Amino acid sequence: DTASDAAAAAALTAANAKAAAELTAANAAAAAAATAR
């Protein structure tokens, strides 16, 4: 169904975009911290 699939696509886009920012920031912080030792 078009409206259902457009809503599912919007939720997947939002979830993956948000997760990409969160893991990018967490990974950069953890890697910089580990490297500093």
Image (cartoon, rainbow, N blue to C red):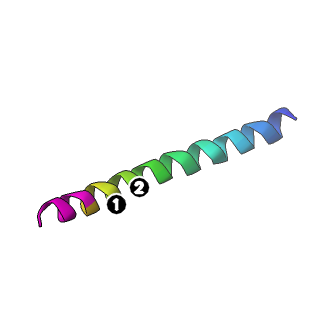
Residues rendered magenta in the picture = 31-37
Q: Is residue 19 depicted above or below 4 in this figure?
A: below
Residue 11 position within the rendered picture, expressed as x and y whole percent measured from the top left:
65, 48
In the rendered structure, the answer to whether residue 4 lies left or right of residue 19 reads: right
Q: Residue at x 19, y 65 (%)?
A: 33
Q: Which residue is mark 1?
A: 26
Residue 8 lies within the magenta run = no
Residue 24 position within the rendered picture, expressed as x and y whole percent measured from the top left:
36, 51
SS at mark 2?
Answer: helix
Q: Residue at x 20, y 64 (%)?
A: 34
Residue 5 position within the rendered picture, expressed as x and y whole percent measured from the top left:
78, 38
In the rendered structure, the answer to whether residue 20 lies left or right of residue 37 reads: right
Q: Nearer the viewer, residue 20 or 30?
A: 30
In the rendered structure, the answer to whether residue 1 lies left or right of residue 18 reads: right
Q: Residue at x 73, y 44 (%)?
A: 8
SS at mark 1?
Answer: helix
In the rendered structure, the answer to whether residue 25 lies left or right of residue 1 reads: left
Quarter in which the N terminus is drawn: top right
Q: Which residue is mark 2?
A: 23
Quarter in which the C terminus is drawn: bottom left
